Image (cartoon, rainbow over the protein chains, first blue to last red):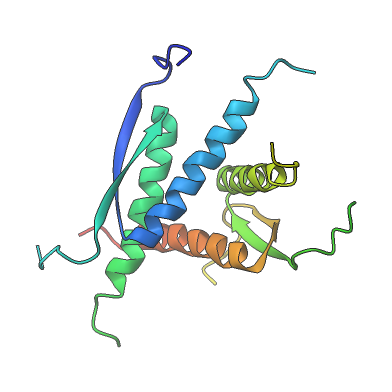
Length: 42
Length: 42
Length: 42
Length: 42
């Protein structure tokens, strides 16, 4: 998808299920902002 | 180690190396606090 | 602005300047996602 | 307390009460780790 060979990917183990959902939200949140910088500037 | 069969473990992919180190710190930070609740109360 | 009398607002002291910028990013990140749920569904 | 005139302090507004408690935990978590580096090395 758009040559996902961009930044190197990694992986992290997160104990607890409630904590996992929380971290996942942070990752998606930053990705959302970063995904907005991919839109042509106004 | 102390029957690590406690809470279910999970895994999350984190793009970017700088971001990875940052999330890892948060995971270790919470584990540090949680690891302190394992000490007998004063 | 759109009756900002929504959820109660709060305040938190954050030591360190580098850490401050980091937390601010997380707050803006979540606000960005929450700000996206305000758009009419497709 | 130990000359708290160390790093400059700041403040951040966090909307939502549930979110506030969450950020507060992160701040305390990092402070806990940083507070551990204040102990003489083994």
